[PDB]
């Protein structure tokens, strides 16, 4: 048996030959050993009660008689075991594996990843006791997993540059901030980072300390779909480049630009993004059509792999490489572009958490594997979601589970905005990527429960679990940031005017009240929160639920007010309340997170007090449906619920060739309007997504609902998180009818069905 008594020091055995990442994690554990146990860690090289090392690099691993074997030639893996003498042995298959083993002990001591990052103060313990029989083995489901700090102009950049690591250089997020991010990634078992790179920010590799900090923490520096060669064009090109960022006309200067960087960074953990786009987003320069944009890349790959040959590794298949066909580059891939088989292909979601492309059997068999770049934060059309992090766990789950199952297993990268306040989604994503089976065996719901129970208490989480659930479900219906019914990047000013959502007075009141109850629950449960966890509560529960409530209030009272059904002052008050909540955020823990929260990111009209004006049109009328179903109200047919997914948490997958069968009685009127609501996801194989509707055997009507590019329908789809198909059918006038919905393609997910009489 292994026993650590609190108040007492502890000796840790670790060879001095071990990679920086091992020593860094040791520091982190010692920090936690002190916090949790009041126990000062002493690093010897020979004698310890906790022994740590990598396979065939440490004499120490051999000399305590543990059967490591399962670890031999294996990726990022560790064994934890107690030797017969009662010592804790941490045996990693490689250096990262050793690091992750050490940090597992830190999880066992009850230290949250958000210890620092959401002030989840670890509890103190009297003793820590693991069995002589305790034996854990771990390894990652996904090989590269990481985050991208992006859209940082209104949170993480000013917070770093003025509050946490105050700097006089214009947009500096310096070494000390990055060490903090890398702790978070270590504790999340992530290994990869795409640094901030917006024009407002100092490029990572042009910041003194940053590169060396990444080496200390063992993080693969990668970069985005427009940052080819560890090279942030967005910020660096205007500093260090010459002439146009154009390979067709100015390739020598572009090549040089890349080269200098590959030179300074070649003996370092880097993931090299291949290819070429614009300075930030947009077309590449110098080519117009996809046929000319293909000729370019062919030229670009050959030279880019060239530099890698010359400064990194004579065999380039030993250099890790990614190609990311995001936005218009997906088209240029699909025009038959040849990408060398060792290069990881990185698929992209549509910025609203719907993956655009799943690997064909061919792409899947490629030696370089397949990755995904996913968004829980975004700036773009039809509207930014940058303030709160409200994407449903249920949607993240179902998309990312599908991604792994469809063979996207090499590389997962999350766009996380400012990190806060997406703490929960980030950890879900990172858990998925670390151990998919564990997350899959538990609910979506069991994951969130375990998380709230861990961060708040059991007693708080008893009241709060259903609140978070309701939070994510109402945000799925319409995010806080979408409540103005406005658009961004539309090139017409009318889409910037706040305007009615197409909902009835009844639906508005119903929504207003559901939010009221949420705010009330959150207020009451506040005093049942342990003393060391009040800041985490404001950060993780109280700010997002009450922020969201007050946004709905501001915009919904405003809508009632336009139609002379409410007083405008309630809208302003709701506005004032968001302000107050944001002041509190920015003043918690002295002002630890001062500037991290901006309730007007990018100064979008939706975040302002609402312009007072009287409606011209009337309110949407409430419309009586004859029938209203979820996928399981069906008689005949099998459809597995996607756990908490859809408008009423009951969306379900109808597998290809299966059907659901709905039944209903005697109607009036000539005809029936069938209103079918589906998850607006994208085709899993092929380009299709369709279903058939059949009233009373009557020869299936064939209905498609996939979208292409960023069309008007796709814009509608992602704002409301439903594809919508209406159909009018003739009744016979039978007295008993059946409606059969059959799936023709793979990933068809039904959410709602409504009926409506009509003539
Ligand atoms: Ni943000």
Image: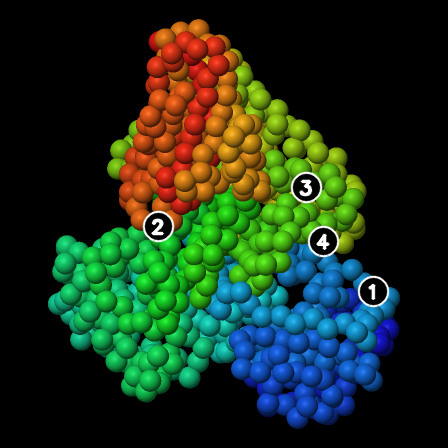
Q: Vertical placement of 584 versus 281: above or below?
A: above
Q: Residue at x 58, y 22 (%)?
A: 510
Image spot of residue 54 (x, y percent) = 61, 84
Q: Please state if 523 lies on the left or on the right of 85 as rendered.
A: left
Residue under label 1, please give it: 125
Residue under label 2, please give it: 685
Residue under label 4, please give it: 454
| Circle 4 SS class | helix
Q: Please state if 366 lies on the left or on the right of 554 as rendered.
A: left
Q: How many angstroms separate mark 1 from mark 4 (CA)? A: 15 Å
| Mark 4 or mark 2: whose residue is earlier in sequence | 4
Residue 119 picture quarter: bottom right
Image spot of residue 190 (x, y percent) = 54, 66
Q: How many angstroms separate mark 4 from mark 2 (CA)? A: 39 Å
Q: Are marks 4 and 2 in contact (CB under 8 Å)?
A: no
Please indicate, yes or no, whether residue 373 appears anywhere in the rendered image.
yes
Q: How many angstroms separate mark 3 from mark 4 (CA)? A: 12 Å
Q: Residue at x 58, y 32 (%)?
A: 549
| Mark 1 or mark 3: whose residue is earlier in sequence | 1
Residue under label 3, please give it: 465
Q: Please state if 427 lies on the left or on the right of 151 as rendered.
A: right
In the foreground, 223 or 717: 717
| Mark 3 or mark 2: whose residue is earlier in sequence | 3
Residue 380 picture quarter: top left
């Amino acid at each position: 048996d292994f026993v650590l008594q609190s108040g007492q020091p502890v000796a840790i055995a670790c060879s001095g030959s071990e990679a920086p990442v091992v020593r860094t994690s040791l520091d982190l554990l010692s920090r936690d050993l002190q916090t949790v146990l009041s126990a000062t860690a002493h690093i010897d090289t020979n004698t310890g009660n906790i022994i740590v090392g990598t396979i065939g690099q440490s004499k120490l691993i051999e000399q305590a008689g543990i059967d490591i074997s399962a670890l031999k030639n294996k990726k990022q893996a560790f064994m934890l075991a107690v030797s017969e003498d009662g010592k804790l042995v941490v045996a990693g298959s490689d250096s990262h594996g050793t690091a992750y083993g050490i940090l597992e002990i830190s999880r066992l001591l009850g230290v949250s990843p958000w210890e620092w990052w959401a002030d989840v103060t670890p509890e103190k313990k009297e003793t820590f006791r693991l069995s002589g029989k305790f034996r854990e083995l771990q390894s990652p489901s996904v090989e590269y997993r990481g985050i991208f700090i992006n859209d940082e102009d209104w949170g993480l950049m000013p917070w770093s540059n003025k509050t946490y690591e105050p700097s006089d250089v214009k947009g500096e997020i310096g070494p000390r901030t990055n060490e903090r991010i890398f702790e978070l990634l270590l504790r999340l078992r992530a290994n990869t980072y795409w640094p901030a790179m917006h024009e407002c920010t100092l490029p990572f590799f042009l910041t003194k300390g940053n590169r060396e900090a990444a080496k200390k923490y063992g993080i693969f520096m990668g970069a985005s779909h427009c940052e080819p060669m560890a090279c942030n064009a967005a910020g660096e090109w205007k500093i260090r480049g010459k002439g146009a960022y154009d390979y067709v006309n100015n390739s020598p200067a572009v090549y040089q630009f890349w080269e200098d960087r590959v030179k300074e960074v070649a003996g370092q953990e880097i993931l090299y993004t291949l290819g070429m786009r614009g300075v930030h987003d947009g077309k590449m320069q110098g080519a117009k059509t996809v046929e000319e944009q293909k000729a370019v890349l062919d030229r670009v790959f050959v030279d880019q792999r060239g530099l890698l040959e010359k400064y990194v590794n004579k065999d380039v298949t030993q250099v890790p490489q990614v190609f990311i066909p995001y936005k218009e580059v997906l088209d240029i891939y699909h025009a038959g572009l040849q990408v060398p088989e060792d290069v990881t292909l990185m698929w992209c979601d549509d910025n609203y958490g719907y993956i655009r492309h799943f690997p064909t059997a061919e792409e899947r068999a490629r030696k370089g594997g397949n990755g995904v770049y996913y968004h829980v934060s975004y700036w773009g059309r039809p509207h930014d979601h940058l303030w709160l992090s409200t994407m449903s766990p249920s949607l993240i789950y179902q998309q990312m589970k599908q991604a792994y199952d469809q063979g996207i297993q090499k590389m997962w990268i999350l766009n996380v905005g400012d990190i806060k306040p997406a703490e929960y989604q980030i950890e879900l994503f990172m858990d998925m990527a670390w151990n998919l089976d564990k997350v899959s065996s538990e609910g979506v719901t069991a994951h969130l429960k375990h998380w709230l129970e861990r961060e708040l208490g059991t007693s708080c989480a008893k009241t709060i679990l259903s609140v978070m659930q309701e939070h994510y479900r109402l945000a799925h219906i319409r995010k806080p940031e979408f409540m103005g019914n406005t658009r961004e990047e539309e090139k017409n000013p009318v889409y910037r005017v706040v305007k009615d959502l197409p909902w009835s007075e009844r639906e508005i009141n119903e929504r207003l009240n559901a939010y009221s109850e949420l705010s009330e629950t959150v207020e009451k449960a506040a005093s049942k929160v342990p003393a060391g966890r009040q800041s985490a509560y404001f950060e993780l529960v109280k700010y997002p639920v009450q922020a969201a409530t007050q946004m709905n209030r501001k915009l919904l009272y405003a809508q009632l007010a336009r139609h002379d059904k409410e007083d405008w002052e309630k809208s302003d008050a709701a506005y004032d309340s968001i302000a107050a909540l944001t002041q509190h955020y920015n003043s918690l823990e002295n002002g630890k997170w001062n500037r991290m929260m901006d309730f007007k990111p990018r100064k979008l009209p939706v975040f302002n007090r609402v312009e007072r004006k009287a409606a011209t049109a009337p309110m949407t009328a409430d419309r009586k449906a004859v029938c209203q179903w979820n996928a399981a109200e069906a008689k005949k047919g099998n459809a597995i619920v996607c756990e908490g997914l859809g408008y009423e948490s009951k969306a379900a997958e109808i597998k290809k060739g299966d059907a659901l069968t709905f039944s209903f009685g005697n109607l009036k009127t000539d005809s029936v309007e069938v209103d079918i609501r589906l998850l607006p996801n994208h085709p899993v194989h092929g380009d299709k997504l369709r279903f058939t509707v059949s009233l009373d055997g009557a020869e299936p009507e064939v209905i498609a609902y996939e979208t292409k590019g960023r069309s008007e329908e796709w814009k509608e789809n992602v704002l409301r998180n439903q594809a919508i198909r209406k159909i009018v059918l003739p009744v016979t006038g039978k007295k008993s009818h059946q409606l059969v919905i059959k799936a023709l393609d793979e990933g068809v997910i039904l959410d709602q069905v409504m009926l409506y009489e009509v003539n």
